Length: 49
Length: 49
Image (cartoon, rainbow over all chains, first blue to last red; front, top):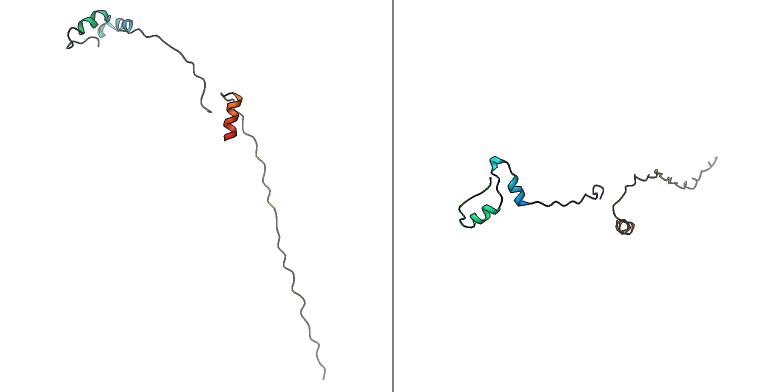
């Protein structure tokens, strides 16, 4: 109880589509629309880095 | 011819014992700390302690 203090409770929305659209060019940015529909067609593929 | 006088020992001395007392300095209150709980809860806490 000596050490405890009220912490600033915060919330943040994280958009997976935006994050995967935003990663550096050498990591290969991609929106999930054009890889979700193609990895479902064949599961042996991979996307992102 | 002279009959000597004979000395009678006196009663034994009453042994006495000394009983002294000890004194110790009183304590001092530590530094009070601001809590997080409201008074009824910090009181149920302290009362338990």
